[PDB]
Length: 126
Ligand SMILES: Cc1cc(/N=N/c2ccc(S(=O)(=O)Nc3ccccn3)cc2)cc(C)c1O
Image 1 (spheres, rainbow, N blue to C red):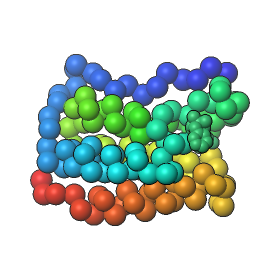
Image 2: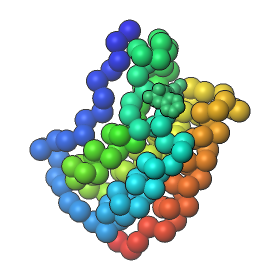
Image 3: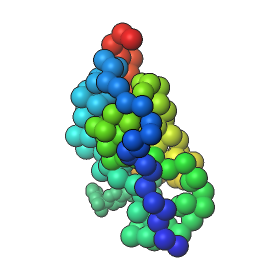
């Protein structure tokens, strides 16, 4: 199997804005996660070809990753903070669906997700 195309990151037909929450999501949340020691599995789409995971996109129908999220933020692709938060949650969920408890990658996801949730608890006002 081929990899699916990556998620769209730009769309001139989708309205754009910058909000304090979206700024925080890029500058604090994304950037903090991105530099973490456990970020590497999550910095780009899962390359099921390169990793020889033929079933990955048979199981995961809503792929998402931080590279995509970063580009969406940088492109002002999101209108609502919740769209971005949802993308992060989808990314984590995919990991938990595909992988098993105690797998290194699941422990990595848990740790990154705990940091993510901590940071979104600090989202500034609307
Ligand atoms: C979310 C997710 C990621 C993944 N594999 N991801 C990668 C990402 C990057 C590399 S890397 O080889 O470019 N960089 C590395 C590889 C190992 C340690 C540090 N950096 C390898 C696997 C595999 C699975 C199932 C999965 O559910």
